[PDB]
Amino acid sequence: ARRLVMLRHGQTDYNVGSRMQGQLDTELSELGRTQAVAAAEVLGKRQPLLIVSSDLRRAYDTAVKLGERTGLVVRVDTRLRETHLGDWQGLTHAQIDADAPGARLAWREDATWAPHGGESRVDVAARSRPLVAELVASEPEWGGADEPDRPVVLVAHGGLIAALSAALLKLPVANWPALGGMGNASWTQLSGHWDFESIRWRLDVWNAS
Amino acid sequence: ARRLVMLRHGQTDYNVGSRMQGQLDTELSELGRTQAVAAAEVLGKRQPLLIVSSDLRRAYDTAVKLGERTGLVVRVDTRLRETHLGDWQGLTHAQIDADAPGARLAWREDATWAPHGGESRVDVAARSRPLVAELVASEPEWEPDRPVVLVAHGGLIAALSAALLKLPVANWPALGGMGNASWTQLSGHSIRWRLDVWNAS
Ligand code: VN3
Ligand code: VN3
Image (tube, rainbow over all chains, first blue to last red; front, side, top):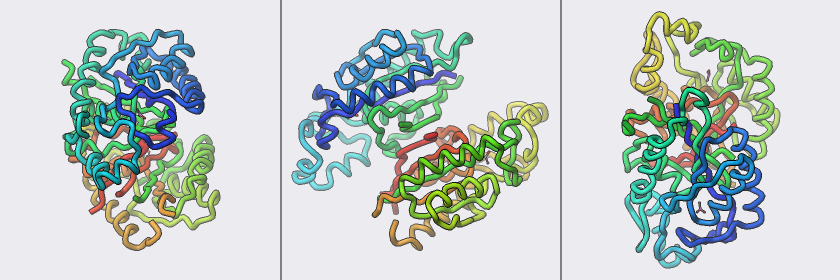
């Protein structure tokens, strides 16, 4: 079995202000940096095989602390970026609700709906799922005989993680909103048991702190 | 929206020996009581509204440590019992696999399959889900972030959670087994449930 760990970036100042980011490249807050230190310790002990991060700095900075704790290089991939949120980037929840009452809630319940200029959950899965497939192909050590519990660690964002997870689990799109919201520096683990499609993923942990 | 928290029982002696329990009333082990304390600590802080426990002692006792921690009567409902596992109750993994090779694994992948004499995951969801809807009706208070806590079992939690999420039966095996004294949180916003936490320790 292949263990896949997915870590949401630590707290940013925008998170503190309930302000939407998307692919705006915001900074970790001080608290966010200490969160990343704490998470690296926990995940470091699990002895990751590999670290792949979103190139957005809030994720990348989170990933670098795990790299320091484990002596692994941090690989970077734009396909792990958070959902592009188009017109909503830079606005707060309150601001969005004032303009479009009910649009946020509606967005949340429809995995095919994108904000104007942005991405849907389905779009994000379409870019991120093949990356997991590439790592299955490129990392023979993963779930291999020697050390089969050593996880691949993807460091990213909450939207990306829900989308990628639902897609790996092969939930129908209509059910993707069943997956909730990750905490800052919280993680999710899937296991892939066994062609890439033949892999059967299950959810071991959603949103551990 | 309403928070629903579901806690699996602490470790039993049967768990250490990979021995199936079902609705056999087995006991918490030493380590299991310890686990139940620690979990009581964490979950007490979220200021639970109310507690329902399976009447099985491994679950009931687990619930008690939280009840003590926060001062509420641990309500009991037999509808929170673990999957009845028929012929498998009392048998070990090694034992089941020797008699019916591949049945145990295949069972995990089919929410509709029951051990002979026992219940399927679909059966378990149908009997336990009415308890949640009853608590929706009979409990006005739903401070709306205070959680309702169900203390129960790994099978029951997976099945009930999948049913609340309205996952298709075919996808119910997407949910992996809960750790001992680990918990899950659903949020209900008919109501649409989402998964906030699966198998936190
Ligand atoms: O705040 V995020 O990009 O998960
Ligand atoms: O082994 V338990 O009844 O979840």
